[PDB]
Image (cartoon, coloured by chain):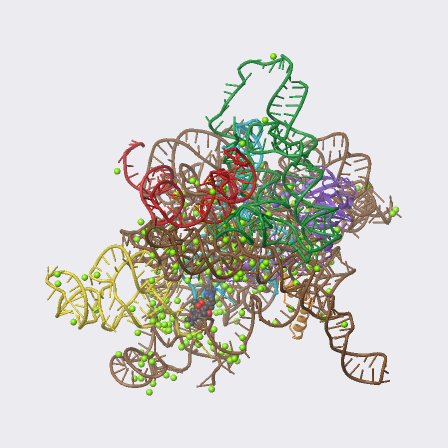
Chain colours: A orange, B purple, C cyan, D brown, E yellow, F green, G red
Amino acid sequence: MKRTWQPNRRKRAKTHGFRARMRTPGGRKVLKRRRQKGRWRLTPAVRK
Amino acid sequence: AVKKFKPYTPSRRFMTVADFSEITKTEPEKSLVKPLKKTGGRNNQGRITVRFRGGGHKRLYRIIDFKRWDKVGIPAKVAAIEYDPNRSARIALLHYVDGEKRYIIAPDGLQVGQQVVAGPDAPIQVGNALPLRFIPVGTVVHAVELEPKKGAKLARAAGTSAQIQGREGDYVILRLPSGELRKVHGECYATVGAVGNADHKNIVLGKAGRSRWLGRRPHVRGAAMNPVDHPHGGGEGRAPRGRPPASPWGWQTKGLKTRKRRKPSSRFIIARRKK
RNA sequence: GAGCUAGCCCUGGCCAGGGUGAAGCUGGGGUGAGACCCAGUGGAGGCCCGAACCGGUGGGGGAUGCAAACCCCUCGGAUGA
RNA sequence: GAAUGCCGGCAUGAGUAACGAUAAAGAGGGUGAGAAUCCCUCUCGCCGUAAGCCCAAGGGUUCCUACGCAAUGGUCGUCAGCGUAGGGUUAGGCGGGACCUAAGGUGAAGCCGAAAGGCGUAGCCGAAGGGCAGCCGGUUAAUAUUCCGGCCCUUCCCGCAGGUGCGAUGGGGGGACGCUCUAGGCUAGGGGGACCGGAGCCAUGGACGAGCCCGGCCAGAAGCGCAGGGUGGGAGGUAGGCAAAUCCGCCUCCCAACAAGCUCUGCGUGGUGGGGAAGCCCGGGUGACAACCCCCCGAAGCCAGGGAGCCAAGAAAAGCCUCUAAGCACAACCUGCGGGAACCCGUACCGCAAACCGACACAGGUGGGCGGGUGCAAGAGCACUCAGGCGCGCGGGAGAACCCUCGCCAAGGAACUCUGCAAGUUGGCCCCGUAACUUCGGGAGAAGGGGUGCUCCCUGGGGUGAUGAGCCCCGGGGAGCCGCAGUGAACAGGCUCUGGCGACUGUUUACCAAAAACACAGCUCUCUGCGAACUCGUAAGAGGAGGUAUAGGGAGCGACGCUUGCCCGGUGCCGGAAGGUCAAGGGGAGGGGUGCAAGCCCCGAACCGAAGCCCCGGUGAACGGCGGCCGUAACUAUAACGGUCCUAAGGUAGCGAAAUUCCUUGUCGGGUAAGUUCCGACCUGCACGAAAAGCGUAACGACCGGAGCGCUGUCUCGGCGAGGGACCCGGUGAAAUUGAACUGGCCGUGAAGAUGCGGCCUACCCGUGGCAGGACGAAAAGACCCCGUGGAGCUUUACUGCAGCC
RNA sequence: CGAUGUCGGCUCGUCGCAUCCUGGGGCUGAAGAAGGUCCCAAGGGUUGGGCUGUUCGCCCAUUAAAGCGGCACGCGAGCUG
RNA sequence: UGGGAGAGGGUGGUGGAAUUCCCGGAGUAGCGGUGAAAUGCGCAGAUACCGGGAGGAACGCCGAUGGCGAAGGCAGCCACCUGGUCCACCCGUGACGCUGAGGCGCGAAAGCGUGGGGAGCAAACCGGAUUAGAUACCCGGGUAGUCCACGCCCUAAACG
RNA sequence: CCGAGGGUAGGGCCCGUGACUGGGGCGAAGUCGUAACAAGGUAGCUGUACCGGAAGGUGCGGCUGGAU
Ligand SMILES: CC[C@H]1OC(=O)[C@H](C)C(=O)[C@H](C)[C@@H](O[C@@H]2O[C@H](C)C[C@H](N(C)C)[C@H]2O)[C@](C)(OC)C[C@@H](C)C(=O)[C@H](C)[C@H]2N(CCCCn3cnc(-c4cccnc4)c3)C(=O)O[C@]12C
Ligand SMILES: [Mg+2]
Ligand SMILES: [Mg+2]
Ligand SMILES: [Mg+2]
Ligand SMILES: [Mg+2]
Ligand SMILES: [Mg+2]
Ligand SMILES: [Mg+2]
Ligand SMILES: [Mg+2]
Ligand SMILES: [Mg+2]
Ligand SMILES: [Mg+2]
Ligand SMILES: [Mg+2]
Ligand SMILES: [Mg+2]
Ligand SMILES: [Mg+2]
Ligand SMILES: [Mg+2]
Ligand SMILES: [Mg+2]
Ligand SMILES: [Mg+2]
Ligand SMILES: [Mg+2]
Ligand SMILES: [Mg+2]
Ligand SMILES: [Mg+2]
Ligand SMILES: [Mg+2]
Ligand SMILES: [Mg+2]
Ligand SMILES: [Mg+2]
Ligand SMILES: [Mg+2]
Ligand SMILES: [Mg+2]
Ligand SMILES: [Mg+2]
Ligand SMILES: [Mg+2]
Ligand SMILES: [Mg+2]
Ligand SMILES: [Mg+2]
Ligand SMILES: [Mg+2]
Ligand SMILES: [Mg+2]
Ligand SMILES: [Mg+2]
Ligand SMILES: [Mg+2]
Ligand SMILES: [Mg+2]
Ligand SMILES: [Mg+2]
Ligand SMILES: [Mg+2]
Ligand SMILES: [Mg+2]
Ligand SMILES: [Mg+2]
Ligand SMILES: [Mg+2]
Ligand SMILES: [Mg+2]
Ligand SMILES: [Mg+2]
Ligand SMILES: [Mg+2]
Ligand SMILES: [Mg+2]
Ligand SMILES: [Mg+2]
Ligand SMILES: [Mg+2]
Ligand SMILES: [Mg+2]
Ligand SMILES: [Mg+2]
Ligand SMILES: [Mg+2]
Ligand SMILES: [Mg+2]
Ligand SMILES: [Mg+2]
Ligand SMILES: [Mg+2]
Ligand SMILES: [Mg+2]
Ligand SMILES: [Mg+2]
Ligand SMILES: [Mg+2]
Ligand SMILES: [Mg+2]
Ligand SMILES: [Mg+2]
Ligand SMILES: [Mg+2]
Ligand SMILES: [Mg+2]
Ligand SMILES: [Mg+2]
Ligand SMILES: [Mg+2]
Ligand SMILES: [Mg+2]
Ligand SMILES: [Mg+2]
Ligand SMILES: [Mg+2]
Ligand SMILES: [Mg+2]
Ligand SMILES: [Mg+2]
Ligand SMILES: [Mg+2]
Ligand SMILES: [Mg+2]
Ligand SMILES: [Mg+2]
Ligand SMILES: [Mg+2]
Ligand SMILES: [Mg+2]
Ligand SMILES: [Mg+2]
Ligand SMILES: [Mg+2]
Ligand SMILES: [Mg+2]
Ligand SMILES: [Mg+2]
Ligand SMILES: [Mg+2]
Ligand SMILES: [Mg+2]
Ligand SMILES: [Mg+2]
Ligand SMILES: [Mg+2]
Ligand SMILES: [Mg+2]
Ligand SMILES: [Mg+2]
Ligand SMILES: [Mg+2]
Ligand SMILES: [Mg+2]
Ligand SMILES: [Mg+2]
Ligand SMILES: [Mg+2]
Ligand SMILES: [Mg+2]
Ligand SMILES: [Mg+2]
Ligand SMILES: [Mg+2]
Ligand SMILES: [Mg+2]
Ligand SMILES: [Mg+2]
Ligand SMILES: [Mg+2]
Ligand SMILES: [Mg+2]
Ligand SMILES: [Mg+2]
Ligand SMILES: [Mg+2]
Ligand SMILES: [Mg+2]
Ligand SMILES: [Mg+2]
Ligand SMILES: [Mg+2]
Ligand SMILES: [Mg+2]
Ligand SMILES: [Mg+2]
Ligand SMILES: [Mg+2]
Ligand SMILES: [Mg+2]
Ligand SMILES: [Mg+2]
Ligand SMILES: [Mg+2]
Ligand SMILES: [Mg+2]
Ligand SMILES: [Mg+2]
Ligand SMILES: [Mg+2]
Ligand SMILES: [Mg+2]
Ligand SMILES: [Mg+2]
Ligand SMILES: [Mg+2]
Ligand SMILES: [Mg+2]
Ligand SMILES: [Mg+2]
Ligand SMILES: [Mg+2]
Ligand SMILES: [Mg+2]
Ligand SMILES: [Mg+2]
Ligand SMILES: [Mg+2]
Ligand SMILES: [Mg+2]
Ligand SMILES: [Mg+2]
Ligand SMILES: [Mg+2]
Ligand SMILES: [Mg+2]
Ligand SMILES: [Mg+2]
Ligand SMILES: [Mg+2]
Ligand SMILES: [Mg+2]
Ligand SMILES: [Mg+2]
Ligand SMILES: [Mg+2]
Ligand SMILES: [Mg+2]
Ligand SMILES: [Mg+2]
Ligand SMILES: [Mg+2]
Ligand SMILES: [Mg+2]
Ligand SMILES: [Mg+2]
Ligand SMILES: [Mg+2]
Ligand SMILES: [Mg+2]
Ligand SMILES: [Mg+2]
Ligand SMILES: [Mg+2]
Ligand SMILES: [Mg+2]
Ligand SMILES: [Mg+2]
Ligand SMILES: [Mg+2]
Ligand SMILES: [Mg+2]
Ligand SMILES: [Mg+2]
Ligand SMILES: [Mg+2]
Ligand SMILES: [Mg+2]
Ligand SMILES: [Mg+2]
Ligand SMILES: [Mg+2]
Ligand SMILES: [Mg+2]
Ligand SMILES: [Mg+2]
Ligand SMILES: [Mg+2]
Ligand SMILES: [Mg+2]
Ligand SMILES: [Mg+2]
Ligand SMILES: [Mg+2]
Ligand SMILES: [Mg+2]
Ligand SMILES: [Mg+2]
Ligand SMILES: [Mg+2]
Ligand SMILES: [Mg+2]
Ligand SMILES: [Mg+2]
Ligand SMILES: [Mg+2]
Ligand SMILES: [Mg+2]
Ligand SMILES: [Mg+2]
Ligand SMILES: [Mg+2]
Ligand SMILES: [Mg+2]
Ligand SMILES: [Mg+2]
Ligand SMILES: [Mg+2]
Ligand SMILES: [Mg+2]
Ligand SMILES: [Mg+2]
Ligand SMILES: [Mg+2]
Ligand SMILES: [Mg+2]
Ligand SMILES: [Mg+2]
Ligand SMILES: [Mg+2]
Ligand SMILES: [Mg+2]
Ligand SMILES: [Mg+2]
Ligand SMILES: [Mg+2]
Ligand SMILES: [Mg+2]
Ligand SMILES: [Mg+2]
Ligand SMILES: [Mg+2]
Ligand SMILES: [Mg+2]
Ligand SMILES: [Mg+2]
Ligand SMILES: [Mg+2]
Ligand SMILES: [Mg+2]
Ligand SMILES: [Mg+2]
Ligand SMILES: [Mg+2]
Ligand SMILES: [Mg+2]
Ligand SMILES: [Mg+2]
Ligand SMILES: [Mg+2]
Ligand SMILES: [Mg+2]
Ligand SMILES: [Mg+2]
Ligand SMILES: [Mg+2]
Ligand SMILES: [Mg+2]
Ligand SMILES: [Mg+2]
Ligand SMILES: [Mg+2]
Ligand SMILES: [Mg+2]
Ligand SMILES: [Mg+2]
Ligand SMILES: [Mg+2]
Ligand SMILES: [Mg+2]
Ligand SMILES: [Mg+2]
Ligand SMILES: [Mg+2]
Ligand SMILES: [Mg+2]
Ligand SMILES: [Mg+2]
Ligand SMILES: [Mg+2]
Ligand SMILES: [Mg+2]
Ligand SMILES: [Mg+2]
Ligand SMILES: [Mg+2]
Ligand SMILES: [Mg+2]
Ligand SMILES: [Mg+2]
Ligand SMILES: [Mg+2]
Ligand SMILES: [Mg+2]
Ligand SMILES: [Mg+2]
Ligand SMILES: [Mg+2]
Ligand SMILES: [Mg+2]
Ligand SMILES: [Mg+2]
Ligand SMILES: [Mg+2]
Ligand SMILES: [Mg+2]
Ligand SMILES: [Mg+2]
Ligand SMILES: [Mg+2]
Ligand SMILES: [Mg+2]
Ligand SMILES: [Mg+2]
Ligand SMILES: [Mg+2]
Ligand SMILES: [Mg+2]
Ligand SMILES: [Mg+2]
Ligand SMILES: [Mg+2]
Ligand SMILES: [Mg+2]
Ligand SMILES: [Mg+2]
Ligand SMILES: [Mg+2]
Ligand SMILES: [Mg+2]
Ligand SMILES: [Mg+2]
Ligand SMILES: [Mg+2]
Ligand SMILES: [Mg+2]
Ligand SMILES: [Mg+2]
Ligand SMILES: [Mg+2]
Ligand SMILES: [Mg+2]
Ligand SMILES: [Mg+2]
Ligand SMILES: [Mg+2]
Ligand SMILES: [Mg+2]
Ligand SMILES: [Mg+2]
Ligand SMILES: [Mg+2]
Ligand SMILES: [Mg+2]
Ligand SMILES: [Mg+2]
Ligand SMILES: [Mg+2]
Ligand SMILES: [Mg+2]
Ligand SMILES: [Mg+2]
Ligand SMILES: [Mg+2]
Ligand SMILES: [Mg+2]
Ligand SMILES: [Mg+2]
Ligand SMILES: [Mg+2]
Ligand SMILES: [Mg+2]
Ligand SMILES: [Mg+2]
Ligand SMILES: [Mg+2]
Ligand SMILES: [Mg+2]
Ligand SMILES: [Mg+2]
Ligand SMILES: [Mg+2]
Ligand SMILES: [Mg+2]
Ligand SMILES: [Mg+2]
Ligand SMILES: [Mg+2]
């Protein structure tokens, strides 16, 4: 049957992307925490 | 004269449609239409605030002339009578001798080919707009401004009329379509005669799908729900109300008056409505 | 977090083929005029049968599965909410 | 040493299940250390509205080549979507951007919010919608509308020529629209040809033939032709289109009107440029100077912004045209020609799948286009086949039980069983024919029947064309032939009678319930006078609705038919300007503290003082409720009648052992040989009853009862057969579970059901196929139940707050 | 209660005997045939259907007879639901 | 041809009286009701009186023993549209007549459907009385209905 | 070929019969009330509508076959 992951590059960038996160207090804290943890990538990869 | 159907389906047995007998032109005036943003009962938060709305036929909005004191003294000609899906009444296209074109809601008995006019000295003739203080007492009237220059507000549904009952200073007394007696300022504009399409109240939708075409989604009974949803929810099997009948939000729905007490227009409502 | 699922909004797309034969129109009859009758034309419908498509009724299989809901037979809708 | 402990290692189950669709394989020849598994050839089978082809998403080198086989691949492997390396994606015209707007998002102005932030007009962003200029062939190992060839085209810059009041983010026109049905002419596509081109073939009994087999096109500028769309001309006035306006709008006048004229598309032709089969020989080359023509069928595509009907009344904005304003009329714009200029990103490959979503090379999921031929009434259905693509990444044997999927069955025919569950039957088309009842539509495919192939003869009408031939499509009559059987294969209703429920088509518990549940048109009550009520929000602001009582919210009922009684004492709601109670506040009789005193300070009675509550009324399609005992008639029985107690009032009509009836399989009738079910009645209704509607109702139902016919492997009652497994051999090789085990029966005993204790009996050691009685067998720290001053959802006239409202 | 699956049916048996039938007996208010009642006896046998989930029961047609109980109301790692 | 009388019919308009309700005034201890009463209403200010307003239905005197129509039936007044009928003249047609099974149309009230309207009245219904009871007569309330439009129903002591 | 008739299926008319149910007629001396006949103690009858143990009552309209 239809499973739950249905990749969509535009959806991925627009929901979890860098500019989405920066527009929002909670989104910025996400960047602050993922940068403080030292993640090699701050938002999901998507090819545009 | 609503048209019936032979019972060749379960639903055509009861469906009735309007005769459309007065309509003379079947596509609207391109200079006077604009896109009607369908809301679906959602507000600017995206929240449903009016339940069971959505999914009706696409529509264009006809811009209507609810302030006819716009063009005092300038006669117009009734050019067409048209279908408007945004209202129950039909609409009338006026070609002003100006060359300007406008839509009014079409009163009962209006005829394509006649002239109409707006102003304090207009003939007491169907389709003419005057300030209320100049219409002779007794005349039935429609598209009535509630405050001067603010625009027609009252009696615009198909087949409705207000009657002029008397004067009192700057204010005339009206019998509204609801039967309430209210004072309205004499400088408020109004249009002689009742609204057309009186047979509108006699249309039998006939099937569920016709309600869907109108943008009306199915209404769910509170008694058919659960307690988390509604005061009437729950129960083993069916259940009477088991409390004073209530809305989804708790307030009582049989008789509880809801007009605000200290409202400033109370000084102008003479008799609350009938029946 | 609505890339699943629910509703709505905008913009596109899809619905083999066959059956039934509403209104109206015309002709004929009828009548004071009518209603109305008959034939023709007409092509209506949450109409009918049936693929795609959308469903998931009964039964069997599967049950450390091909599958954390599937498979076979059968069955519902299929111009419409 | 124990925590169903944690981490890791290794065992048991076991050489066990399994190796992923039952579309299917065999041989020869290669290669190589090694071959069922890689390569080639021949044979066989499977898909063919796909299991073929082309896009889009998503994936991201998986593409091509060489070199490999440790691991990955469910076996093998020389192979590979694997490892290493090298190569490979080419655009002014295709797609997106340098264009436009849609929902929505964002947001100078402005509004709001403790902060964060929330709104918000314009404007900006936003596409698979609008707009915009490329077609055919060739070429690579791998890209091609991109490279190359042929023929076309767009925009920008500059120049020349002719012309013109030129000029825009401003005005206007246009763009610009639904659903169903649909005309005319075309094209895509396809069928046929005794014509045109072709390497050949003559078999095995016949055929050297009007024989077989193969193919008979594609693109094309201007012009021309056909078929379509779009479009009135001139004048005078003018106050409207937020300045202007010669435009547009309105009025008058003349002329033109199924036309024509102008314009824009499609199709055809078109200079010219390409393509070109079987067969044969090593992807090539020949065929080949290949030919390239006629007839028919014919789109759902094109002309298109076509036509008609209908109600539910069917985006925007730019490009484009027109009008003018500042301006400028050495300019500028328009037309034609010439030269120049023309950027960024994508382009490999998979793409119904082994490359995407499902942990897997996973029987599942994934949007658009193309989808040939014949026959079956049609069709995308069905069978077989073209092009093309596959045989599903373990095999070889055997021919036990048992399982699955399938085929047949003597006699019987539902006797099976909770139930005809399941499986038979029936099955398309054409014709004859068709009942109660009905809302006159239907019920209806009712039911039940007859026909169905092939040959020959005669004949009616249509389409094309020409009226004729040919081709094609619809028929009618007559005489025959064969078989068990002519929709000869495949696809394709079993039917009737009668209840309950729900009117109906719809909807639902993704993944145990599809229903009688929800919804539904319709009915009623009620709120709402518009800055509406109501709803979301602290607000601003939205929705309601750019609506206005024939409208909008809420509630119940639930098509339709006939109906919907009595109770307002209690709760609710509605009305009541009196009265009663009532907070803050007002008032200040009179008290108290303190100071020598002026004063300062504190307590405070009467009385004035809202909503609410009390009180007085109303109100049932508001919450709700609608009795008991005793007596009575000239056979008996029963009580039309009466007495009395209580109530706010004592259940009306209709219905009733019911989806409701406890006693209960009530009683009687019906159906049956027999009927706890069913149907029809009766009525002492435990405990129906009138919009939580009462009683009916044609039609409808994958709903639930009862019956009958047809037919059956359901059964008496089983039998045989098929294939996939199970079994044996080679390859690979899990699992839950597991205190350890050297693990028998009886009768006892034991914490009360003993392989393990007693006593007897029985028993050589170890396996394989099987069966499930035991190991209180496995699985999940019982869901039932209780307990915990454990938790959560839910209710209310529990308590106490809060929103909201007054 | 860190789980002993719980009615009935079906299938498959097996055991007890307080025996339904068949074998052998005594008594009889046993003439005969037919019964009644008690004693011995468990070898074998103990039907098909309608109703109901039913066990049980009633009924139909037969029968030599249409037994009564146990085996976790025998038997769901055997099936049904 | 010329005339006449008439609530004959249909449509639209419109006038005064009266009842009810509402607003204002003024006013106070009862009103209403019956055989007698009670229910009811009234100091929350009724009844009785005055001014205003709304709304429905019916049409006093004229009015008669009258008139018109086929019957049912028709009553303020105005206009429009339309029927029948009677008289006078003796002008036209030349038996074109009578009746009338079927058919068709009309058809009081009540009743039915979908809308509207609703003052008064009033089935049902509630209450107060009466009574042995009183599911009645009498009284106080009261819903259909009475009224309008359209559509059915088609009955009657539809009688002379 | 036709053909008595037999069979299958589905209709129409009639007759008998059926739990139970509707009212009707009749029946020496039953129970309830008193609707009608006099103004029958509310004049009666009437079509219709609604209600009530029963006769009946009431509404709307009509008739005199109504009395004073
Ligand atoms: C069919 C397979 C399942 O077995 C049964 O379902 C079985 C018939 C039982 O019911 C089993 C016997 C139960 O035990 C009993 O529990 C009782 C409470 C007590 C009993 N004894 C103790 C007496 C005890 O034996 C229990 C609890 O199973 C629920 C066992 C318990 C260990 C389980 O939960 C167990 C893990 C089950 N489960 C959940 C099933 C969820 C629902 N589901 C069902 N089908 C699908 C499905 C269908 C199709 C496709 N995909 C999924 C999903 C599974 O995935 O596998 C199961 C074993
Ligand atoms: Mg899904
Ligand atoms: Mg998706
Ligand atoms: Mg995307
Ligand atoms: Mg997206
Ligand atoms: Mg976002
Ligand atoms: Mg983003
Ligand atoms: Mg912040
Ligand atoms: Mg910050
Ligand atoms: Mg990481
Ligand atoms: Mg780094
Ligand atoms: Mg992130
Ligand atoms: Mg109809
Ligand atoms: Mg009809
Ligand atoms: Mg109209
Ligand atoms: Mg526009
Ligand atoms: Mg909006
Ligand atoms: Mg918004
Ligand atoms: Mg709402
Ligand atoms: Mg909504
Ligand atoms: Mg309209
Ligand atoms: Mg409206
Ligand atoms: Mg006003
Ligand atoms: Mg309505
Ligand atoms: Mg609509
Ligand atoms: Mg509704
Ligand atoms: Mg509902
Ligand atoms: Mg409920
Ligand atoms: Mg519920
Ligand atoms: Mg919730
Ligand atoms: Mg609640
Ligand atoms: Mg409740
Ligand atoms: Mg409930
Ligand atoms: Mg209940
Ligand atoms: Mg419920
Ligand atoms: Mg209720
Ligand atoms: Mg209750
Ligand atoms: Mg409540
Ligand atoms: Mg409120
Ligand atoms: Mg009001
Ligand atoms: Mg999505
Ligand atoms: Mg379809
Ligand atoms: Mg027509
Ligand atoms: Mg349909
Ligand atoms: Mg059909
Ligand atoms: Mg299924
Ligand atoms: Mg599904
Ligand atoms: Mg089945
Ligand atoms: Mg399946
Ligand atoms: Mg199938
Ligand atoms: Mg089917
Ligand atoms: Mg169908
Ligand atoms: Mg279809
Ligand atoms: Mg639709
Ligand atoms: Mg220890
Ligand atoms: Mg463990
Ligand atoms: Mg632990
Ligand atoms: Mg561990
Ligand atoms: Mg571990
Ligand atoms: Mg470990
Ligand atoms: Mg380690
Ligand atoms: Mg290990
Ligand atoms: Mg091991
Ligand atoms: Mg081992
Ligand atoms: Mg084993
Ligand atoms: Mg296994
Ligand atoms: Mg497996
Ligand atoms: Mg298959
Ligand atoms: Mg196949
Ligand atoms: Mg081989
Ligand atoms: Mg090698
Ligand atoms: Mg190999
Ligand atoms: Mg090898
Ligand atoms: Mg193979
Ligand atoms: Mg090979
Ligand atoms: Mg094919
Ligand atoms: Mg995309
Ligand atoms: Mg991947
Ligand atoms: Mg390897
Ligand atoms: Mg290897
Ligand atoms: Mg290596
Ligand atoms: Mg491997
Ligand atoms: Mg694998
Ligand atoms: Mg490449
Ligand atoms: Mg190019
Ligand atoms: Mg640039
Ligand atoms: Mg902000
Ligand atoms: Mg954006
Ligand atoms: Mg954009
Ligand atoms: Mg675009
Ligand atoms: Mg382009
Ligand atoms: Mg081109
Ligand atoms: Mg020019
Ligand atoms: Mg347009
Ligand atoms: Mg438009
Ligand atoms: Mg569009
Ligand atoms: Mg439509
Ligand atoms: Mg072409
Ligand atoms: Mg063809
Ligand atoms: Mg002007
Ligand atoms: Mg050559
Ligand atoms: Mg299409
Ligand atoms: Mg088009
Ligand atoms: Mg068109
Ligand atoms: Mg816009
Ligand atoms: Mg200037
Ligand atoms: Mg100059
Ligand atoms: Mg650039
Ligand atoms: Mg490429
Ligand atoms: Mg697929
Ligand atoms: Mg693949
Ligand atoms: Mg595989
Ligand atoms: Mg797959
Ligand atoms: Mg072909
Ligand atoms: Mg066919
Ligand atoms: Mg295979
Ligand atoms: Mg396959
Ligand atoms: Mg395989
Ligand atoms: Mg073997
Ligand atoms: Mg198979
Ligand atoms: Mg055979
Ligand atoms: Mg047999
Ligand atoms: Mg049978
Ligand atoms: Mg038989
Ligand atoms: Mg049976
Ligand atoms: Mg049954
Ligand atoms: Mg069959
Ligand atoms: Mg068949
Ligand atoms: Mg057949
Ligand atoms: Mg019948
Ligand atoms: Mg019939
Ligand atoms: Mg029947
Ligand atoms: Mg019936
Ligand atoms: Mg009929
Ligand atoms: Mg048939
Ligand atoms: Mg038929
Ligand atoms: Mg043959
Ligand atoms: Mg069928
Ligand atoms: Mg239902
Ligand atoms: Mg239903
Ligand atoms: Mg019902
Ligand atoms: Mg019904
Ligand atoms: Mg449907
Ligand atoms: Mg479910
Ligand atoms: Mg569930
Ligand atoms: Mg689930
Ligand atoms: Mg299921
Ligand atoms: Mg269903
Ligand atoms: Mg539901
Ligand atoms: Mg429902
Ligand atoms: Mg329904
Ligand atoms: Mg209803
Ligand atoms: Mg209503
Ligand atoms: Mg709120
Ligand atoms: Mg708005
Ligand atoms: Mg319904
Ligand atoms: Mg309901
Ligand atoms: Mg009926
Ligand atoms: Mg009450
Ligand atoms: Mg009360
Ligand atoms: Mg009350
Ligand atoms: Mg004070
Ligand atoms: Mg209660
Ligand atoms: Mg109560
Ligand atoms: Mg009643
Ligand atoms: Mg009963
Ligand atoms: Mg019974
Ligand atoms: Mg019943
Ligand atoms: Mg009951
Ligand atoms: Mg019972
Ligand atoms: Mg019972
Ligand atoms: Mg019985
Ligand atoms: Mg019987
Ligand atoms: Mg009884
Ligand atoms: Mg109930
Ligand atoms: Mg029914
Ligand atoms: Mg259904
Ligand atoms: Mg169903
Ligand atoms: Mg049966
Ligand atoms: Mg039978
Ligand atoms: Mg068998
Ligand atoms: Mg076999
Ligand atoms: Mg061996
Ligand atoms: Mg091995
Ligand atoms: Mg291996
Ligand atoms: Mg040990
Ligand atoms: Mg040991
Ligand atoms: Mg052992
Ligand atoms: Mg042993
Ligand atoms: Mg013990
Ligand atoms: Mg023991
Ligand atoms: Mg032992
Ligand atoms: Mg020992
Ligand atoms: Mg010991
Ligand atoms: Mg021992
Ligand atoms: Mg021992
Ligand atoms: Mg022994
Ligand atoms: Mg074994
Ligand atoms: Mg065992
Ligand atoms: Mg245990
Ligand atoms: Mg065991
Ligand atoms: Mg056990
Ligand atoms: Mg635990
Ligand atoms: Mg526990
Ligand atoms: Mg547990
Ligand atoms: Mg317990
Ligand atoms: Mg406690
Ligand atoms: Mg405690
Ligand atoms: Mg607790
Ligand atoms: Mg919970
Ligand atoms: Mg336990
Ligand atoms: Mg355990
Ligand atoms: Mg258990
Ligand atoms: Mg366990
Ligand atoms: Mg003897
Ligand atoms: Mg004897
Ligand atoms: Mg003895
Ligand atoms: Mg024995
Ligand atoms: Mg038992
Ligand atoms: Mg029993
Ligand atoms: Mg015997
Ligand atoms: Mg016997
Ligand atoms: Mg036993
Ligand atoms: Mg025992
Ligand atoms: Mg047990
Ligand atoms: Mg027991
Ligand atoms: Mg027990
Ligand atoms: Mg048991
Ligand atoms: Mg058992
Ligand atoms: Mg089981
Ligand atoms: Mg069991
Ligand atoms: Mg077990
Ligand atoms: Mg077992
Ligand atoms: Mg066991
Ligand atoms: Mg069950
Ligand atoms: Mg006073
Ligand atoms: Mg009124
Ligand atoms: Mg007369
Ligand atoms: Mg004469
Ligand atoms: Mg009448
Ligand atoms: Mg009384
Ligand atoms: Mg008395
Ligand atoms: Mg008379
Ligand atoms: Mg014979
Ligand atoms: Mg009397
Ligand atoms: Mg009398
Ligand atoms: Mg009398
Ligand atoms: Mg009465």
Residue E14 point in image, percent of width and height: 26, 71
Classify residue B231 as left or right of residue G3: right
Residue D715 point in image, percent of width and height: 31, 58
Classify residue D394 as left or right of residue F113: left
Residue D573, located in which quarter of the rendered image?
bottom right
For the question of whether residue A1 can be seen, the reply is: no
Residue drawn at (68%, 72%), measured in percent from left and top? A32
Say which of E23 and A32 sits in front. E23
Residue drawn at (73%, 44%), measured in percent from left and top? B191
Residue E28, located in which quarter of the rendered image?
bottom left
Q: Quadrant of the N terminus of chain B?
A: top right
Q: Is residue F139 placed above or below E12 in the rendered structure?
A: above
Ligand 232 falls in which quarter? bottom left
For the question of whether residue B3 can be seen, the reply is: yes
Classify residue B251 as left or right of residue D233: left
Residue drawn at (71%, 52%), measured in percent from left and top? B269
Q: Please tell me how many numbered marks the rendered image carries.
A: 0
Q: Is residue B243 placed above or below D337 in the rendered structure?
A: below
Residue D190 point in image, percent of width and height: 51, 43
Say which of C62 and B68 sits in front. B68
Residue D106 point in image, percent of width and height: 71, 61
Classify residue E29 as left or right of residue F70: left
